[PDB]
Image 1 (spheres, rainbow, N blue to C red):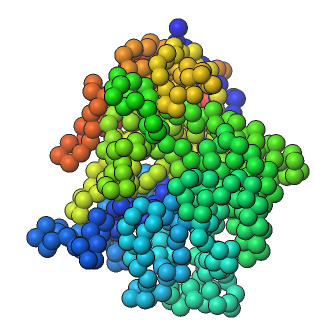
Image 2 (cartoon, rainbow, N blue to C red):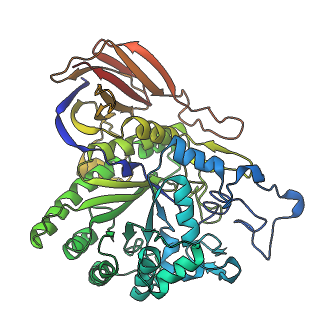
Image 3 (spheres, rainbow, N blue to C red):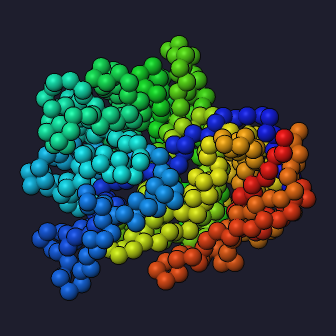
Length: 524
């Protein structure tokens, strides 16, 4: 019989704001046609097969900052989501990216084949435009080194270019390109992108990567000792992860892991099972994060590292590899079920706030994204709303422990191992954040509850240990009768948040296939 206890005195950790981070890759319409305007040679056109003039709508000049950025997209990422950090220039793209192609006067920038996904890249948007965009967006840059074709020397020159404050060739080059003296001061850098993957350019074994990354990490820190470096992990639970952490833990600050739900081989003809395959998927990540926490502490013991080492979950999201393809620029239109998967993802990061310091939604615009653009406008996908609600209400507080009794799902999971190795996922899924208003010292409790069950509703007594709960509760609810309902053009708010205020009586009913964020007052 379902029951939810919350323990505001049992602190997990402060919620890191970088759990709400973003990610932009030079893929499809993420950059050109996304944060920047489309051209007659944006993806999917090219300079030698352009769009016909008759069929090309341009982005109005009104919609652009003076540097050429989309102001409406900026409004969503900065003013609605308050994204604090963005990973760039990618996941797979970066492993054959030469950063020197993307700086200097624009007419001297080298067009390159795009090997990871099959296009052409102009490199009109390179390091200085990315930093300038981050400045307008009020976002911290997070840059990934090329560890596919790239060399250590190229990486050291990039750090010098961005962060050097002396009289040295690459710092002077930055000053010449930007007309300013000040360094970019990029604080976060990642040592490669998925070096473990068979699709990756420059794929390596765990031992070969770890040995190389230890050398790169050591030399990069000599150029700028204040930088935060991120080692390339796999999913957190793999042999790769142990090998890499054992070798990097005294040289880096974070460990990067990636996972997508709705992803992977399965019998897609069994449609009745796709719902449960998708919504319970984030259970795989919490199991893997917990394993990774132990591998971190093993490696720290082994090298006598007193500093904490944290996790960057710097690719998470929802991606079916048969829907979002390289041909269509990884475009996937999300349904309401997908938004319950998204809410489950964010609850994982809250519950694991003591180790997850960064999480990056893959991707922030157009690529498998909460946000879809056209040349003249945009719409927010179903998965945008859980992100919006967590970013607004579960940030700037302390994640606290919960104890949740819930019926379990007996069906097929994706990946299939979650059911057997972790256990049957709970229908209900919750996380809690205690928040203190800095101007008034008023104390509130934000409780985010997903009911993943496709058919059962649950009446749930909710008990708050050692606290009086205020008379009124504010409810932010996401629900639709059709789990296949989507947002799209002309139907932008098919799936949207409903908010209301109710009287608190110590229980709540969580409808089938729903997400509910409750805001409770705690009078002193």
